[PDB]
Image (cartoon, rainbow over all chains, first blue to last red):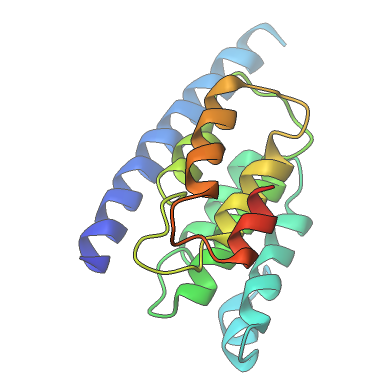
Length: 31
Length: 129
């Protein structure tokens, strides 16, 4: 239960990390 | 803490770990990427104290920057539910301080229900208020 909650948290952490990397690449592209 | 904060958190005891971890976000204020990178490792600990402190750290990191993306929203609405225990004060306070000026009906409607659910002790109720 707690372990699978941690797994889901890790999944969303990876998702948002990739999204943030894309966002900052796009930002630095123009700035 | 940034060098080796795990030992620092562990030598911290009782309820201290909450604030000890939130200090990580305070240090990594306004830096979403750095905060996430330095908080992910501590985000998964056997004791929920460290997890809630990490949630506070992420909320503090998000606070002050109005990024259209809402990593704080996603991560912290994942935990806004009591999860069978009252130790969600950290999540609630983090969400608040992160979205202070946002006034997003999304976060308002996420927070108001959990505020009264027959299981939100006065601590949780005050934090969410």
